[PDB]
Amino acid sequence: GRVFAPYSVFKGKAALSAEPRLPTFNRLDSGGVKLNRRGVIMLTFWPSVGERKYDWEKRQLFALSATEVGSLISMGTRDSSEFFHDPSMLSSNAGQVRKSLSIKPNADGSGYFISLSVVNNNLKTNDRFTVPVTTAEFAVMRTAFSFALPHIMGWDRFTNR
Amino acid sequence: GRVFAPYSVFKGKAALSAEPRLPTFNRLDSGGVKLNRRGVIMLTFWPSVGERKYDWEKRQLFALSATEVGSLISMGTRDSSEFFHDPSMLSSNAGQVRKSLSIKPNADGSGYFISLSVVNNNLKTNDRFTVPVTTAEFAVMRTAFSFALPHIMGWDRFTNR
Amino acid sequence: GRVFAPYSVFKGKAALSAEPRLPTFNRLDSGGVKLNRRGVIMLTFWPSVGERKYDWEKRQLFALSATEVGSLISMGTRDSSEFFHDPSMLSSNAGQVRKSLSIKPNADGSGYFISLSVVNNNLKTNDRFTVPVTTAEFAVMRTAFSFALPHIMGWDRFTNR
Amino acid sequence: GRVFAPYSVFKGKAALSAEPRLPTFNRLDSGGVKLNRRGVIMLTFWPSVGERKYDWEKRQLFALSATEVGSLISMGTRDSSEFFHDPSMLSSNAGQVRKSLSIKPNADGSGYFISLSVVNNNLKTNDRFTVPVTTAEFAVMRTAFSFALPHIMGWDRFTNR
DNA sequence: AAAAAAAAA
DNA sequence: AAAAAAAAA
DNA sequence: AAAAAAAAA
DNA sequence: AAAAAAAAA
């Protein structure tokens, strides 16, 4: 069944959570197994209400694909990347919701700012959660993501006994 | 049985697929186990027919050995490597078919071009599939290959319980 | 049950031991599993009495969290980090005991000094164990810690079969 | 039982083989498990007799400890390391046999020379096998050794389920 | 709740 | 066949 | 369908 | 014996 062991970062204005969603497989009728829906690294952002307390119900999600992960783990100190996602893509509700994840170095080079933006043209809202991430914390993600990458790709199945 | 979870890259003129083929073992009569045929990282190239559609039947293969993998994961941004293979080697049909895989950085340093060339003197054909690969994508291969390397070498068997 | 395979470094004035403490989980009533208490990399320091012999009973501990680990594995040759811990935190006995772990490069760049300081205002004691660590040894920790990081985070549970 | 999957390099004058020997454990009477004898990365050198053929019976061994491994995987392009071993150490036959492993970059920086020297004062012999190693091959060892390091340390036992 | 799609045993 | 030793549940 | 070979318990 | 806490299925 499910497993809940997210790496989390709690800061002044918002919280960040990251955990792997494994790929789904389909047992073929040839006997073997085929990778079906792809795994990701899910990112959850949510706001801090009141004093050191976080409103879990106003949360927004961002699914990192294998390639977006590779883009992140290969980031240099002075590098920055930005990903743009439409949840309801190739679907009926396209163009309506627009997510954009940005990773930028801060002035000091003492880390990055990781912010999620969500623009919903249906509900007429504009949300933005930003979380500062230190070098040590981003080292955690880098390493944890690297480790997780083969698994979300399904490559952990290629095992000798 | 078999497992199908290839990392794939689909571009304008062709598609690239990479997946590990595990080594085969032979149970000795001493009780232990001996590595027999070696594992590789198989690369499959195939052409794009019509509009965003790929002719799976005109595909060519290239098997990366452990050492060729190590050559790839240790490539710098400005580096390039070229591998040359004869499928029917030390065999009757040698010199007939000639494969050459090249990995070159593009001008921008924004990635590499990965091309497969196949020259068949029997069928009198000359094929060449090239796929551009971004930094993020090549980061995926680098990481996925690194992870896979111990497995195709059989070293995943050396495990404490 | 428990497992005892610490990486150890024995030097002139003191000994250093490092081993992973895995996270604890709670099986939810939803069926799945939830990470409970977090894993760490435990560091044990203890003094050398007499000639090449070490007083196991005067030992002090320091628990590295995931983020402190990431801080360590991302250290450059010329880098240094210092962690400050209060064992009895958010508790009744706070402010009483104070631990500080320092990792500093030595002049030669031939490694680091890893020292633990413990100031106990209850028992009125002031302890300090320092252990020199070569590049090769610190390479061992770096690698061993990197490997261990996903496990103490609970991410080794995200596995395809 | 035993497992035989060595990474091997065959060159003009000699052959090199590398494979992990796992640590031995002792089940305590407390229930848990304790690491006993330490694992290593065994290196086997042997001479080439005649034309492309190798005299398996004149082979010499060198056991890499965890720390020696860390020294090797942290080697730069222009770096070189030398290890010195006495097989019959803290024993009756000490000082008699003397092994020295050297890893040096070649002029081109196109790899290293890995040579084993064995001086036996009992049998009055002086042996020396050298094997050139390319960047790609040394990348294989680096990666394969890194992967193996946690295992020979016993850290592969710290696993969540 | 999650950006999807292209080959195929 | 292998460089070993130091604490300890 | 795949570049192979060299030692050996 | 260990620096803890914040959401939640």
Image (spheres, coloured by chain):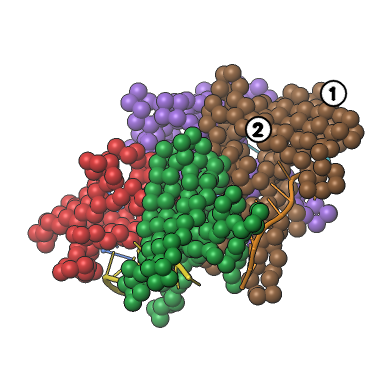
Chain colours: A green, B red, C brown, D purple, E yellow, F cyan, G blue, H orange
Residue at 44 percent across and 76 percent down: it is A26
Circle number at residue A39: none
- Picture residue at 67% right of the left edge, 36% below the top: C83
- Lateral position of residue B77 relative to residue C20, left or right: left
Q: Residue furthest top?
A: C107
Q: How many marks do you count on the picture?
A: 2
Which residue bears the numbered disc 2?
C82
Q: State the residue position of label 1.
A: C50
Residue C116: where, in percent of width, then height?
73, 31
Q: Which of D123 and B50 is in front in this view?
A: B50
Identify residue type, mark 1.
Answer: Gly
Q: Which residue is at the far bottom? A: A29
Towards the viewer: B39 or E2: E2
Residue D122 at least partly seen: no
Which residue occupies the extreme left position in the image?
Answer: B124
Q: Can residue D104 be seen in this view?
A: yes
